[PDB]
Structures are given as structure tokens and as C-alpha cells.
Amino acid sequence: KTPADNIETADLSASVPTRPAEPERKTLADYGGYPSALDAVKQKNDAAVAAYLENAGDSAMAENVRNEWLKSLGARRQWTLFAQEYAKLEPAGRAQEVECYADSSRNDYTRAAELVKNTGKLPSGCTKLLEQAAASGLLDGNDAWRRVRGLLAGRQTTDARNLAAALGSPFDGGTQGSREYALLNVIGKEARKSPNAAALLSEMESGLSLEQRSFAWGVLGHYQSQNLNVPAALDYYGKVADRRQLTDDQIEWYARAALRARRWDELASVISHMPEKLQKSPTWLYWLARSRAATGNTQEAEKLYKQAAATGRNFYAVLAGEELGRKIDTRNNVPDAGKNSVRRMAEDGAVKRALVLFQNSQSAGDAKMRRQAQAEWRFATRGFDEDKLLTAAQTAFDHGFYDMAVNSAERTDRKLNYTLRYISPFKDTVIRHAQNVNVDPAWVYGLIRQESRFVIGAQSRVGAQGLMQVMPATAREIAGKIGMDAAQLYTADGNIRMGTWYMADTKRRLQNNEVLATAGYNAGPGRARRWQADTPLEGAVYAETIPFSETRDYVKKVMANAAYYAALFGAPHIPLKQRMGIVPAR
View: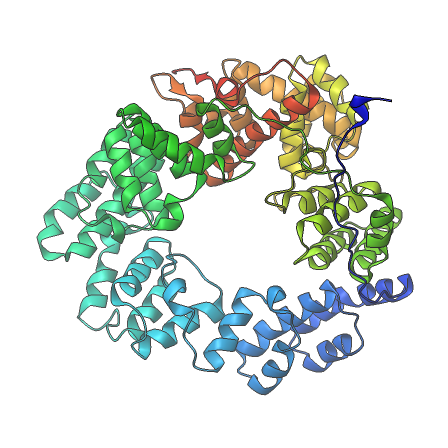
């Protein structure tokens, strides 16, 4: 037999790392002293930190302590010890602030030209690198003063004051810096919301430089845009003479206002003034392609859709694919990892160290230890080629380290295993609870993937708990409605029951719309409703124009996830543009 047997071979590489392994006892002994070494850094007990590191294995625990130690040594100008320890880090493992201290200690301001384009808070070592560059005349002036303005508008007044002084124009100097600081009367956190801010600015405008006027109108346009007063935003942003003076968040909020008003030509113009990095983002490739399509620049729209689709597994890549007639396909383009390579990957010393802390975190119920096991896994799989990442993904999955299976599989660019990118454990529980309140299980899996990456004891710093990241205050509300005890939040079954019921309850309170329910699950229903317009909005326009960055990213990632899960589950096909639909007017 038979012509159907004539099937080609396919292979992932069996090559795995063979880094020296240490006994479990050693891993647990080094974890035993890890929190105390971090406390030693905070207490500036350098001899205690050196003692922890002296016989530590080559682990993320060591790398984390050594990076934290170097931030402290750099702050204290202990450069000889700093240089000795900096050289022990792998380059890929060096923290940003530690690189900045290292280069500023050598008077090397190479990194300042890109750092100074940032308009927000940077770590102290990086803030100081820019101050030193400024005082030596090694910064671009246009970019430096843009950063001073950025820091003023972000309530980083000390950092703005320090940078203006390093530029030679201090806030108390009666020159440019004093004029930039005075502009807080318009650009201050609260001042910019004054009903008189635009009037004040129009009155003072003739006394401002082109750059100061352009940035101040940007500040007022950004506040209006993010407050979803689209016509005011467009009025204020239209007064910006040089759009490149804007911060990245200001220019993206100008594009968002033009998008929400369906001003396609204006949106195309703003996208053209953005930094190249923003232009090449999936969001702006996709929305520029939409603008070209709308304005009858048809071939150019197809070109940009192809660019957006090439960006990978994300909301806008999937929507761009659909405009090209291409539906999501979740068939893998690689074989499964071989079992012998899976076994050998687990013998690698850095992979073993992560699996030892994970397994011990499970047996001892130690959530701090599970967080360090994640850090070990990231350190161990850093720099792996795609075949090794797919092999390590399967290794993690077999051991039940579900988040790390997804972390390794999603790190590839070309070789795609959708079953490890979009894992779906717990179907004997999640599908039942979703069916019981009539909600789409692909949508519930997509939410879980984003909320907890399938970690059953996940806990955000605000206290959101478990697989579905429900807040304790919400669990107590839900418990009072559906006859549960609030502490059921902390069990996987109760957490799935509460989260799925709360998706359905939130959807019922938000015009039964899944985009609004996904926003309201994260931000509350009051906010999701406030963000509706008095006209209908295309779902992707509502999503992109959500004022809170955390919820805007959340809604897109949950919905893209759901589209992948729906294809894996074999549900009748729903295009992502259909899943986003139309958000109703309020």
C-alpha cells in the first residue's frame, strides 16, 4: 500500500542546551536565601549580597539580585565594585537602568539619543545619564526640551527641573526653562481640564515659541480626546503647528479622535507625522490601510493590510487578514516536539532549575516561589532558537507550567504551534460553566488566557484573583446574588463560576453586547457605558478609543484570543470583524 502513504517527512531540531545541572537541594537552598539577599540590597549590606552571590548557581535568582545590587551601587557611585559585578551579567540579562549607570560611569552617552525621545519617567540611572549628556551638550535640544515638557505634563516636576538646569536654563533662571515651567498654568494635570484652559492658552500664545504652543495645544487635545469630547479634541489638536512636538500618547490620541469622527484624511495625515516606530505598529498600519480604502486609494490599502497582517498573532493582524480575504488558520506549520527532545530539554540545568522551583511551589503552596520559577524559565529560554522554544513549550505543558508553555510558544515568529500558543486546560470545568450562562466558550478561554495565562493562583497587585481575575469586592457582590460564599473566589471551580456568571451579568447590563461586556469586566460597567457615543460605533473603533490603556489593550487581546480559540474549537466560523460588530449608541 498505497498512494496516500506517500507523505513527506518534517522535523524540528533535536538540539537542546546541556548547561550544567545542580541538585534540587542546591536550587532550594539558593531560593531560601533569595528574599534575604534582596533585603540586603535595600539595606545596603553589600557584604551580605556578595556572600549570597559568591556560590550561587548561574540562575535568575543571581541575575535578579546582581541587577538590583548594581542599581544600588550605581546610585552610590561604587564604581569599582559596580564594574566587577556588571561584567558578570549576560548582556541580555542586564537591566535597563544598570546599562545606563555602566555607560554614564564611562562617560559614554551613546544611548542618550534614543533615551531622550522618551517623554515619561525613566529609572534614576537613565534619568541621570540624560542629565549628564545635556550638561555636556550631547543632546539634541529639540528632543531635550520636548522631554522637559513631557515630564512637566506627567507630574515629574523634579526630573523636568533637573533636566532644564542641565540644559543651562533652570526653572528659576528667567530664561526658556522658566517659561516652560510657567506653562503649567495650562498644561498641569488639573489645569488642562479647566473650562478656561483653551482661553488662557489662546491669550498667551503670541508669547510662546512654536514648540511650546504645539505642545500645549497637544496637552489640551489629549485631555479632550481621552475624555471622549471628539469635536473639542479635534479643534485643539488642529491648532498644533508642529505635530512632531507631541508626545507619543498625545499623537496617538489625535489619531484616535480622527478615527472616532471617521475623518479619514485627517487620520492619514496624523499617522504620517508619527515616529516610524508608531507608523509600523499593527494599530497604525491597519488604520492607515482603512483610511486609504475609504479614500479610494485601493492598491495602497492592500499593501498596508499585508504589512499589518505580517505582524503576527494580534488583533489588528487578524483584521487586516480579513480585509485581504484571509481567514484565521490555526493549523500548525511545524511538527510536534519529539519526546526524546522534550526529556533532554528538561535535563538542561537552567530548565531543570525552573521546573524544580515550579514543582516545589505546587507541593509547598508557595506563590512567591512560583513567581521566581517563572523568572527562571524566562532566563533559561532566553536566546533559544524557534525549535528549542517549541520544545521547551511542550516541556512546560507536560509539567503543568501552563503560563510558561504559552510564554515559550509565543516567542517564535515563523514556526507556529497554535495548540501551545492557545492552550485550553480545564475544559471539564470552563465549558460547563460557560454553557450554564449561555456565553461563548471561546470568549471565556480568550479572557482567561489574557487574565491569568491559566495560572490558578494568579493575583494582581490590586488583588484580582485566580483564573478569571475577579476582584474580592466583586466576588462578594456575586456571592450575595448566586448563593455562594465569597471565599469560593479562591478555588478554581468557584472562580470559573463567578467569572463566567459575571461576564454574562455584565453583558446583560451593557445592552447584551460582547465588546462592552469585555470592557466592563475589566473597568466596570459604569466606565464601559460612559465610553459609548451617542451614535453607534464600529467595535474596533470603540476598542481603540477606550480611554484607559489597560482596558484598551485588554479588550483587543481578549477578542483576538477568542478568535483563535473559536478556530481551535471548530465552532462555525465568526470573523473577528463580526465578533467586534457594532457597539450601540447611548
